[PDB]
């Protein structure tokens, strides 16, 4: 009921025609479904909109790319806003505010949150159209349900994104590996070792792309391991091994993590 899972992570948002209280209806254009859910922030915005000005909206295509996710360290929530229209003739000073709430589980009716429940945090926006938000989230509220509704204020005009329901834990994006070393085990195997973050409450599966790459012999192999070290049987002498790792949730779908540094090892 009024809850749509994000499947898949790639979605298209389009606003089409049917001040302080100008409401625009935007919907997600999926391959097989068309869902139009309005945010609960404003419910009494039933105000008439002149059709004459709608033609102006025909000349401006409301296409924006905003990516909000939770980092793998479970410390900061990263929201990136980038404008595809890189025009230097107009540098609009826009402010992005992150409105988030963490309601508790109540067994006495599903009460609707009132106005002002969402916390207002002013992000630090740089001069090159980049805004960084640092929201201190306690570890005790990580297992709760988080609902977000992006709000953009520009010249007295308010734009509200459609409500989305998703668990932030399904898109773990850990820090890039550091202190990782490659060596040859005395038993005759290659160890690539890195120090995984200890703040993750569950084991994380890691897939590494490797391929024996000789002058003629080519052999690309892939395996998924969760330990801090990888065991490969009967490493081949005189071969080049490249290591590149990306993150993904063990259970169900997920979002690929950052592209780590690919490292090359050449055996004699």
Image (cartoon, rainbow, N blue to C red):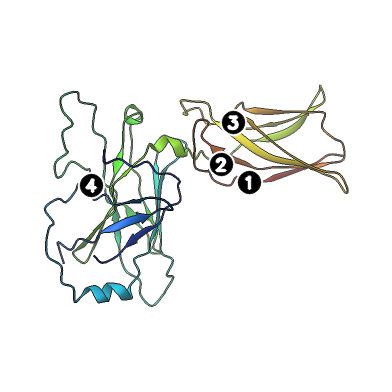
On residue 176, the disc is 2
Residue in the foreground of this view, choosing between 246 and 128: 246
Secondary structure category for the residue under label 1: loop
Q: Residue at x 12, y 65 (%)?
A: 48
Pointer 1 with pointer 2, Cβ within 8 A: yes
Q: Residue at x 33, y 38 (%)?
A: 136
Q: Residue at x 17, y 38 (%)?
A: 113
Q: Is residue 82 above or below residue 140?
A: below
Q: CA distance from mark 1 to mark 3?
A: 15 Å
Mark 2 surroundings: few (<14), some (14-19) or many (≥20) residues within 10 A: some
Quadrant in the picture for the C terminus: top right
Pointer 2 with pointer 3, Cβ within 8 A: no
Pointer 1 with pointer 3, Cβ within 8 A: no
On residue 122, the disc is none
Which circle's residue, 1 or 3, is located before the other in the chain? 3
Secondary structure category for the residue under label 4: loop
Give percent across and percent down for residue 78. 40, 46
Q: Residue at x 53, y 37 (%)?
A: 248
Q: Circle 4 is placed at which residue position?
A: 120
Q: Circle 3 is placed at which residue position?
A: 195
């Amino acid at each position: 009921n009024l809850s749509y899972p994000i499947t898949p992570w790639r979605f298209k948002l389009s606003c089409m025609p049917p001040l302080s209280k100008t409401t625009f209806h935007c919907c997600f254009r999926s391959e097989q479904d068309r869902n139009c859910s309005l945010c609960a922030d404003n419910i009494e915005g039933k105000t008439f909109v002149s059709t004459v000005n709608s033609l102006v909206f025909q000349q401006i295509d409301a296409n924006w790319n905003i990516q909000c996710w939770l980092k793998g360290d479970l410390k900061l929530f990263i929201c990136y806003v980038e404008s595809l229209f890189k025009n230097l003739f107009r540098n609009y000073n826009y402010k992005v505010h992150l409105l988030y709430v963490l309601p508790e589980v109540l067994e006495d009716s599903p009460l609707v949150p009132q106005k002002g429940s969402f916390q207002m945090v002013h992000c630090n926006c740089s001069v090159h159209e980049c805004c960084e938000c640092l929201v201190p989230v306690p570890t005790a509220k990580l297992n709760d349900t988080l609902l977000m509704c992006l709000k953009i204020t520009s010249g007295g005009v308010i734009f509200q994104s459609p409500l989305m329901s998703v668990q932030p834990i399904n898109m773990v994006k850990p820090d890039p590996p550091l202190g990782l070393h490659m060596e040859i085990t005395d038993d005759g195997n290659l160890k690539i070792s890195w120090s995984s973050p200890p703040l993750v409450p569950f084991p994380l599966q890691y897939q590494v792309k490797y391929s024996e790459n000789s002058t003629t012999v080519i052999r690309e192999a892939d395996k998924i391991v969760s330990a801090t070290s990888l065991l490969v049987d009967s490493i081949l002498p005189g071969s080049s091994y490249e290591v590149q790792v990306r993150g993904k949730r063990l259970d169900g779908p997920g979002i690929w993590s950052d592209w780590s540094t690919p490292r090359v090892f050449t055996t004699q």
